[PDB]
Amino acid sequence: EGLVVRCIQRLAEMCRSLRGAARLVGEPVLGAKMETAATLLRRDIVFAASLYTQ
RNA sequence: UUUUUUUUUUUUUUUUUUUUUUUUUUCUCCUCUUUUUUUUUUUU
Image (cartoon, rainbow, N blue to C red; front, side, top):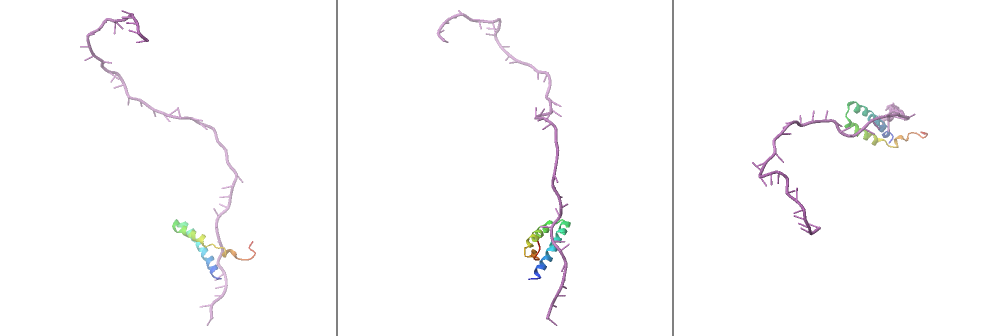
């Protein structure tokens, strides 16, 4: 479980960039379930990162 | 005997206003028959 988190943070970027395409076309049927997936993907272990964040 | 790298949730907020129910039409139009008009009066 070292490459899973990197694959996750790679997936979340394309899901964040598909919103601009769904908005450009004008088809919010997919842009709504994609927004729900985007908010459904953000966990807390992903953002742990390093020790002295703050 | 299969390594290394590919960022992410738009920025903004400390704007004034001194009125008052309604609201706006419909034309001129042959009234039939015993009468002058009876009448005080008293019992409420």
